[PDB]
Image (cartoon, helix red, strand yellow):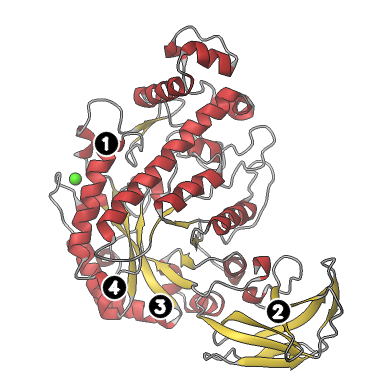
Amino acid sequence: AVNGKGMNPDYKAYLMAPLKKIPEVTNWETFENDLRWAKQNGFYAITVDFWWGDMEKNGDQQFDFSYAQRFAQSVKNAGMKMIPIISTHQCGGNVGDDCNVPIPSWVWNQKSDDSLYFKSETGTVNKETLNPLASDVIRKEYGELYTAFAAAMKPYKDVIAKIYLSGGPAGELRYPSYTTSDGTGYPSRGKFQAYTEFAKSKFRLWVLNKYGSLNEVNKAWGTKLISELAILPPSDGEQFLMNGYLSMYGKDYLEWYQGILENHTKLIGELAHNAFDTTFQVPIGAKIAGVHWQYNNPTIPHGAEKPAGYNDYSHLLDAFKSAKLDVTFTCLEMTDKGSYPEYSMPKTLVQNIATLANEKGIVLNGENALSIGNEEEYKRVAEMAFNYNFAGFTLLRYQDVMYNNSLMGKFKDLLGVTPVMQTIVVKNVPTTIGDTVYITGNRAELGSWDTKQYPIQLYYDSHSNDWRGNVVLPAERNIEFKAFIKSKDGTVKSWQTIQQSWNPVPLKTTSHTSSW
Ligand SMILES: [Ca+2]
């Protein structure tokens, strides 16, 4: 892996449950047996969606956690762990998908205005999640929801491995900028979701708080606004994304726009920490979308990320370290295309989020965006996950490996791995001054034979004159590798005479000694 280190010793693989409830898929007994089969292949937990639309349906605080309870009973019977996702967003909702669980329709009557939903550049209304701008309804409704759930899942705390939160549409912390209804579906650019009277208002009160007076606003934006009512979100998102984003106004609008997400993150992460910390004592996290299309579009750069609210990921992730939340990112199985018309750069995006995240000490969890049909995608996932320090990989979805044994075997081989500590030792290395020793191997956990970005580093032991190093490895898998010397100039001088191997890597901690 990256920075000369190994795979994360805390890597655990997880399975995403289906969208539909288990009794709409199979029965609780073959579900338990499927969970046993999963764990037999390296899955540690099953991550599942518990929808607010189901858990507090009839009215305010007329709660039903019977399904969540029933579901954790089988998880306990199967001797598995689970990761509930308190899904405060809508499931499906439209034509042809495997669910339609709206958010409890009584929520929308808490206000008379438009504080609560979203409206786009062209007037499209979106009601998939509650608008983070309405933080008073969000503190009331989410706080209560979270604590009623902690109360009912307390019997099952020994089966809860972590708790995930929904921060927006599709469980992603972002705005509803890409939808078929708004004419923004992949691979086109999103539209801004700041046109409700309430957002418009909140932008103008923010701007005015920064500058003080309209006069000060016109001074800083180099404009000539008439009234304060002229302080508005962009009227042409296409022009904004084209170049209005470079002006001081543009920079202030996007700071406000991304800022609401950052605040929403500190707020749901506060409410969930209060409610689940004493009782459960588990890591809590939220998800961020991989809006990889229109990344490198020359005309409208980062054309889909900026309407979704992702303008400065370093600053966005900073809201996550402060709220003490883990982050899940989503397209580990994709590669970079970067061409017309989609301008898709997903592998560069995941490499960037991964690096900021490790620089900040935020725990990474990966997810694949789409279903994986071949070994290849699993091998691509293995590369990001193991070379960019992911503490977890959640496979999307259940039925894909559960009703295809060959694919499940490929998963077991590449991603349903258990990390184990091992000492690699290389004797008789002709290391002249300045040189460094590295090992690279065949599996992605050893760098896929790469020597510049991903090799793991070994350190000279002066007492016994060999290069050695405690490497985290895939327990019980066959590995091949070789040591090599990287001269001070980062140049590969030479390699080990004979390629080494461990068939398989023992499950216990040993040492593999070998000579140059
Ligand atoms: Ca409530």
Q: Nearer the viewer, residue 226 or 110?
A: 226
* Label 4 – label 1 distance at C-alpha: 33 Å
Precedes in sequence: disc 1 or disc 3: 3
Specify the label residue 458 is tagged with.
2
Give the amino acid at mark 4.
Val
* Label 2 – label 1 distance at C-alpha: 54 Å
Residue at x 67%, y 66% (from the top left corner): 3
Residue 214 on image: x %, y %: 47, 12
Question: Is 168 positioned to the left or the right of 215 in the image?
Answer: left
* Label 4 – label 2 distance at C-alpha: 39 Å
Above or below, 133 relative to 339: above
Give the amino acid at mark 1.
Asp
Precedes in sequence: disc 4 or disc 3: 3
Specify the label residue 38 is tagged with.
3
* Label 4 – label 3 distance at C-alpha: 16 Å
Residue at x 61%, y 39% (from the top left corner): 302
